[PDB]
């Protein structure tokens, strides 16, 4: 009868594949196969990793259209416990526990999947240090971390993205100071490009959020807390700010470019969700916003285009209700709306790949995912034509 | 880790008892008592060795990476790869 | 935990000064004018921030790893030389204003 | 006359260097 | 197994050396000190086990008694059996003592100091020798009374 060999084989941690397959299969075993318009579908609230915790970022995996990454800042509940909380969530089968977990020594601000590799996850933290994590490996520490130098990011980073295809990829990140830096997924210890974005008289731009035209690399579009929207060419013939927009009086919080591609080219349409309930929409060719969103006040956070519908998007308000907005049918009232129970300080939303459902963040960590109406999810050529004619209204 | 793994595997359904068996049967760990754990886990190890022989009979390169039994009174789970033999006691439902 | 007076090394830089700098940056475009001395102080703090934060993170990392080294006394004799060059660099840098 | 290794790398415990440089900072 | 363990130890040491780290030779020296102490402990354990086996695989030593020209003769005699026993215990010692040293002459090439690295003193070697001498003394005592019969032919009818 062994007493130490089992004890030492338990102490020795060769359980990487063991724990990986156990986690991937036991949640499957939770299935009960015993032989004896808006509507909520799945509500996620991790008690251990989201108890009184504000979601810091949200993303959808293009390679795996079933995986989500959630970010958290430092926890005021307890500073001793790990502060930067990163969550990975899956819909393979219903389960309260998250599929994967991740920790960063600094408060995590933004995080996203990698287009170059279908497993690596990259995240921006409050210390301005991009964080690399490998999903396949069972580790809690960051896999890679950029050096904290003057050339690299030092101010908190709130938007990280990977541009290019799976063979010409480029990881682009923006710091709140205004530094734009490009990395590659292979090495995360040196900025391939680095340049402090400036509009005029050598003053930088306090970028809050960034967006890029769908299907296009370079010629980026950034949003500033100052209340102005800027078009910044990545390299082009001259790097820096390329356009001054009139913008919105309050700070620009959520900026996004149109993504639905069909019989017409609408990739130039820009929507910015400011701090004054005002989702301002326009095109890059016009210096003025084309239309304004006004039903209340006080901070609708972000605006996100529906990937499938050309004239439909979502925007979540700090008051605690998500309103679905379509341009083809309405221009003054939301086509659909719903409020999360308890009226929490709903933070952010993220359109899933191929649409048909929406993911909503919250300040309490209870993220909710649910679908939309079948009569409203599917677009048609009539939708594109009527959107084009409504854009010509003013 | 050990304790966190057992806790997360137990609290997912309020499982009556699970122990980690990284060795070929005869585990000294217990979750309700020594006998019902150890002898039943050894019997499971023998039967899954026989099942591995069964699945290798049709083609030797095949291996049993997943196994579950759901009868009228209990549910038994085991996911062996090379030595990681799991045990789960649960209601049939 | 220790009776002796530990001479813990810190960095002469308040982390909250950048908060004042960002406050000033926000207030300028907000239309509110602050005294020029505050403007100069905030600008200096903002431009000197990356160096200070790099310094503090570097010193924190070096401390953490040196206490990890002294945790295992069997390694400190080998690691002594690297600690020697680190101490020499610290000695060179401390005299600087 | 087989040469023997000379004095090895010294430790110079952190506390001594810290107090020496604290004194140097005080006097500067 | 001792040889492969020492080879891997030396490979790790060489990997450290090629990395051009700091203050290696004294570290190597104290590692050699600890490993030679451990070797002495294992050597005393093995030697005492071999001694109690005498009183660890041991070769079976054999010699015969024969008679030629009506003279009782030994093939081999007792002293050669003693020498074979000494050679066997020498080989048992060399099982451990032939292990090479660790470095960045003959003694320096492979470690021969475990006898001085004896934690229990020369007693274990002394008791092993005492066992050998006791065995050979009893053997020759039996032979003497048994070999006494050869005087019968010396003494004609």
Image (tube, grey):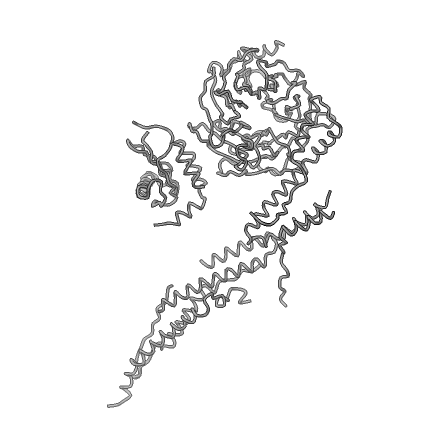
Specify the farthest residue to the left: E157
Specify the farthest residue to the right: C36
As drawn, is B49 to the left or to the right of C5? left
Q: Residue C1, percent across and down?
A: 55, 47
Specify the farthest residue to the bottom: E157
**A377 or A5: nearer the viewer:** A5
Specify the farthest residue to the top: A393
Residue E20 visible from this viewpoint: no
Q: Residue B26, percent across and down?
A: 34, 46
Vertical order, C89 against B10 (above or below): below
Q: Residue A138, percent across and down?
A: 48, 38
Residue E38 visible from this viewpoint: yes
**A161 or A108: nearer the viewer:** A108
Residue E53 appears in which quarter of the rendering?
bottom left
Q: Residue B38, percent across and down?
A: 32, 43
Locate the C terminus of chain A by quadrant: top right
Vertical order, A11 against E57 (above or below): above
Vertical order, A232 against A387 (above or below): below
At a point 62% along the width and 21% down the height, the residue shown is A252
- Number of numbered discs on residues: 0
Residue E50 appears in which quarter of the rendering?
bottom left
């Amino acid at each position: 009868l062994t007493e130490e060999e089992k004890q030492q084989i338990l102490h020795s941690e060769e359980f990487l594949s063991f724990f990986d397959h156990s986690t991937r299969i036991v949640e499957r075993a939770l299935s009960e196969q015993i032989n004896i318009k808006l509507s909520l579908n799945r509500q996620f609230f991790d008690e251990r990793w989201s108890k009184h915790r504000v979601v810091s970022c949200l993303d959808w995996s293009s390679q795996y259209p079933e995986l989500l990454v959630a970010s958290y800042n430092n926890n005021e509940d307890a500073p001793h416990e790990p502060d930067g909380v990163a969550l990975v969530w899956n819909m393979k089968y219903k389960k309260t526990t998250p599929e994967y977990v991740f920790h960063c020594q600094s408060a995590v601000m933004s995080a996203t999947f990698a287009k170059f590799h279908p497993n690596l996850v990259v995240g921006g933290t409050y210390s301005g240090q991009i964080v690399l994590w490998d999903n396949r490996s069972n580790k809690r520490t960051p896999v890679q971390r950029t050096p904290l130098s003057a050339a690299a990011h030092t101010h908190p980073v709130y938007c990280v993205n990977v541009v290019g295809t799976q063979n010409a990829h480029n990881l682009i990140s923006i710091s709140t100071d205004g530094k734009i830096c490009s990395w590659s997924l292979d090495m995360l210890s040196h900025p391939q490009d680095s340049m402090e974005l400036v509009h005029k008289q050598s003053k930088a731009v306090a970028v809050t959020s960034m967006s890029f035209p769908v299907g296009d690399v370079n010629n980026f579009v950034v949003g500033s807390e100052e209340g102005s929207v800027y078009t910044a060419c990545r390299h082009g013939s001259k790097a820096g700010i390329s356009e001054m927009f009139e913008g919105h009086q309050g700070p620009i919080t959520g900026i996004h470019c149109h993504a639905a591609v069909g019989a017409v080219d609408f990739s130039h349409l820009f929507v910015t969700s400011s701090f004054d309930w005002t989702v301002k929409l326009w095109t890059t060719k016009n210096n003025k916003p084309l239309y304004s969103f006004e039903d209340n006040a006080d901070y609708v956070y972000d605006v996100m285009w529906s990937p499938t519908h050309p004239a439909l998007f979502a925007c979540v308000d700090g008051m605690g209700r998500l309103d679905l907005w379509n341009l083809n049918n309405d221009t003054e009232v939301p086509t659909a709306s719903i409020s999360v129970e308890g009226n929490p300080a709903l933070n952010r939303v993220r359109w899933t790949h191929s649409g048909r459902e929406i993911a909503v963040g919250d300040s309490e960590g209870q993220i909710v995912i649910y679908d939309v109406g079948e009569q409203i999810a599917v677009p048609r050529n009539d939708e594109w034509a009527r959107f084009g004619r409504t854009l010509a209204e003013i | 880790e050990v304790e966190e793994t057992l806790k997360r595997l137990q609290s997912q359904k309020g499982v009556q008892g699970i122990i980690v068996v990284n060795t070929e049967g005869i585990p000294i760990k217990s979750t309700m008592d020594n006998p019902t754990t150890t002898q039943y886990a050894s019997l499971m190890h023998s039967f899954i060795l026989k099942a591995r022989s069964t699945v290798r009979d049709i083609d030797p390169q095949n291996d049993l990476t997943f196994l579950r039994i759901r009868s009228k009174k209990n549910e038994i789970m085991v996911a062996p790869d090379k030595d990681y033999f799991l045990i789960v006691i649960q209601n049939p439902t | 935990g220790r009776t002796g007076n530990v001479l813990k090394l810190k960095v002469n830089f308040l982390p909250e000064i950048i908060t004042l700098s960002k406050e000033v940056r926000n207030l300028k475009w907000l239309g509110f004018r602050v005294p020029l001395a505050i403007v100069n102080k905030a600008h200096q703090a903002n431009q000197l921030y990356p160096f200070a934060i790099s310094l503090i993170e570097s010193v924190r990392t070096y401390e953490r790893t040196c206490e990890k080294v002294e945790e295992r006394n069997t390694i400190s004799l080998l690691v002594a030389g690297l600690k020697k060059e680190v101490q020499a660099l610290i000695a060179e840098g401390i005299a600087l204003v | 006359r087989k040469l023997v290794h000379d004095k090895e790398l010294a430790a110079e415990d952190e506390q001594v260097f810290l107090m020496k440089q604290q004194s140097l900072l005080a006097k500067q | 197994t001792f040889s492969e363990i020492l080879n891997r130890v030396q490979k790790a040491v060489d990997d450290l050396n090629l990395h051009s780290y700091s203050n290696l030779p004294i570290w190597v020296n104290k590692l050699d000190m600890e490993i030679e102490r451990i070797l002495g402990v294992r050597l005393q354990a093995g030697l005492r086990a071999w001694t109690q086996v005498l009183l660890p695989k041991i070769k079976n030593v054999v010699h015969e008694l024969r008679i030629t020209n009506q003279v009782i003769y030994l093939n081999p005699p007792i002293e050669e059996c003693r020498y074979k026993l000494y050679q066997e215990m020498f080989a048992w010692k060399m099982v451990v003592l032939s292990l090479p040293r660790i470095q960045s002459t003959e003694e320096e090439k492979f470690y021969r100091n475990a006898l001085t690295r004896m934690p229990d003193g020369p007693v274990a070697l002394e008791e092993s020798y005492s066992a050998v001498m006791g065995i050979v003394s009893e053997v020759e005592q039996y032979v003497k009374v048994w070999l006494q019969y050869q005087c019968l032919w010396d003494m004609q009818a």
